[PDB]
Image (cartoon, rainbow over all chains, first blue to last red; front, side, top):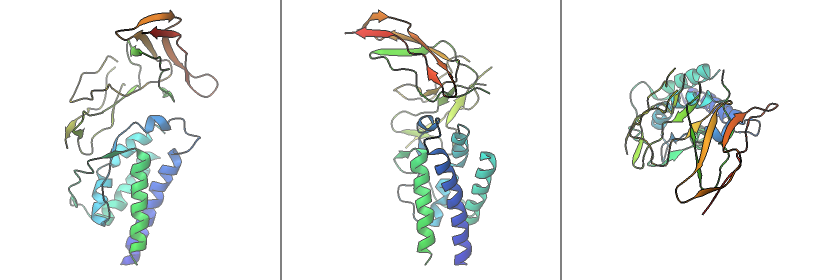
Length: 121
Length: 123
């Protein structure tokens, strides 16, 4: 069902959005610190199958959050992702030849989610 | 529970800084050399807990912990309040002024800040 997938994608994007907005603000002194970690994302993420690269970077995401309940949020996130692309490696994420900060990483995926939701029309 | 310092130690032109030992909680970015990314789904940093915790690992496209296929720029560290680094001019430069040349990340009223070293290295 198109609506199931849309819902899941919305829930997923809102959790990511919660983290991004939650750490990327002037009331967080750890930011600079968090921006030194190199995150990996797809160069051109567009198919739901690409959610494999987000999945492969979740423990790293949970790790940066420790500098900011993460353990529960990431768990929720991870399940939704599996629900959106299964348990098989759906893509060979040797990733972009380029890296990213959590701000970019999250910007990519939040945009990915918002886009696919509209595309599902 | 150690607190991370919001900033890097003061930067002194032509000077480098070194910690003599690392405190419970300093983190070391698992950075890689050019043409090498970190192992898929791999840890982001090592953590001092006494010894280091995680293991860095770079594939291809506490005491000073031992190398791995590291980064040729340095190691990006994250210190905790109470930590001190020591400054010394690099080669080709001498201490013009030698006010305190070490820094401690202190947490005065809320925020953390490093003590300002007073070291000056002229050509």
